[PDB]
Amino acid sequence: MQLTDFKALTFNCYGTLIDWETGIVNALQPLAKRTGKTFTSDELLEVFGRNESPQQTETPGALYQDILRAVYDRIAKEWGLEPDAAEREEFGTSVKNWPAFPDTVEALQYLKKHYKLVILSNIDRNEFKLSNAKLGVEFDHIITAQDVGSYKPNPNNFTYMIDALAKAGIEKKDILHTAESLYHDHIPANDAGLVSAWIYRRHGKEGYGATHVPSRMPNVDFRFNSMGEMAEAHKQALKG
Ligand SMILES: [Mg+2]
Image (cartoon, rainbow, N blue to C red; front, side):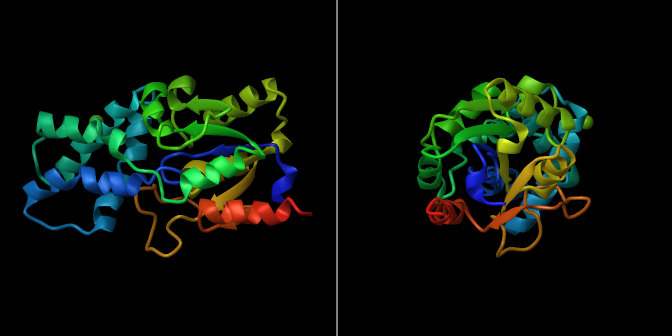
């Protein structure tokens, strides 16, 4: 089993390529100010993480800004605050400000020389374009929650991706699903019969951050602590 066995990398975006945690912590500051309390980053992220996937189940066909607006409402409710419409809009439209991790662009531009690069993301098509402009590559295929009609970890999101790649001549054995989220990505990738690369962005941190808690530890085939480390690994694997 090695990195060079695969023709395509399929990616989570938010949490693996885009640093959604910095974005979410930043975007929650006005609402948090209204509570009178100073939250830690992990507290802000974890209340997001207890709420985002439930919301995606609640409104599976919602565009991502509508998910985020409704997550704002859920967090306000946990905090005893009435939603403020303008504050909710500022939070819900914040993806435009969520930055790439500092290694992401360089790693993607390298890996784009060697793999078809594919997005399988909890996002809608137009919102993703804003993040794609921060990622520095053309993706060969982009599969969004909007395309599927549901959000990961729904198995249909994985089936849709696998089928789309098969039509482009990429067999399932050719795919390496590359992501941080045990819950959203690696558990359903196991169930879908995919090979997995775990990018453990939070390797030096507590808990799961913005990501929902996983029900079990899935089986992963590679672990790298960053995208740059996956790229460095490939540079050596390619010499084999
Ligand atoms: Mg509700």
